[PDB]
Amino acid sequence: KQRMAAKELARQNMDLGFKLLKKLAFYNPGRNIFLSPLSISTAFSMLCLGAQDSTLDEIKQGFNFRKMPEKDLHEGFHYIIHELTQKTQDLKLSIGNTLFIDQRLQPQRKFLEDAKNFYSAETILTNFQNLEMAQKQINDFISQKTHGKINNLIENIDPGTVMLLANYIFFRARWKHEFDPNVTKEEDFFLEKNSSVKVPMMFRSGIYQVGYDDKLSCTILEIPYQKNITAIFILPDEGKLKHLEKGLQVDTFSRWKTLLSRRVVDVSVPRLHMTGTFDLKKTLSYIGVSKIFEEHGDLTKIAPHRSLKVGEAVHKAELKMDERGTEGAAGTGAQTLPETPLVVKIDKPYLLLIYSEKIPSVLFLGKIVNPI
Image (cartoon, rainbow, N blue to C red; front, side, top):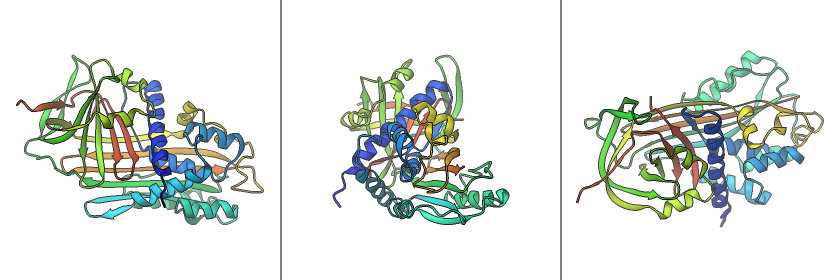
């Protein structure tokens, strides 16, 4: 259907990525940050199905699902999830959800039917009494969907756990124009003006979408993949990283598109491998989402006759960027229990933003202060 809700939803999921990145950088300055905003949004938007009252209110507030009808939210996610799904030529992009429900547990009929519909949720039975058995079963499932990039998603399972909501995303693609390994060579990467470090730097000269933002004082550069997906680099001027971070809003990405223009560019991009792990309980507290992790009898839509709360919530992300392309993967789990050519040299702290063009959505989001 003519569902323009996916676009508005993408606009808000986009803003949510920045929200977390701001707060994460604010509380953890001078460190690498990598995550998948889409993976976290889908997980907690699916969690909104079986929630109500202040628990629902706080989650909608933090994840920007507030200014939106209930209809357009889940209908929007179903559109994004279905359209993004591509296991076609030169582009593997998988995204899905899974409910690890206990046999004894009989959750509401509406919650499951909506989970299976809007989010294509796969029902799977588990025995949480056998912590050692349940863990391996769940970690193996995610390890299989992410082709072994996200291992041991769940480190500790609570005895009282009755359900585990799980989201996974896998991404593999090659550049539209690959870099030549012969040209790549170790060059300086400046953590600061004086301090530098040698890192493997890729290089190619060609037509790139490029521009410069005067408001946030940064250079924009798009390096598209073989199809649909593209990688956007945000290179701020010297001593304006904090200026860039704080200036991130919901309209930021929209503006950057108007500043683009196809030009011949001699781009220098470092090889990038990143691993991210987050305790979502601590993280989501930064955006006001806390009730979901406390007992308030708001998750009755999940269990009609049990007082449930979320115990352990975790997010893990993985990226490997090289000359051939990029391989991305992430997971999210939550337990419920009782002429001179233009030159753009990326040799200093920058932001990386993996974005799907044809299907507006941020698959991954990163802050690189040191590619090693």
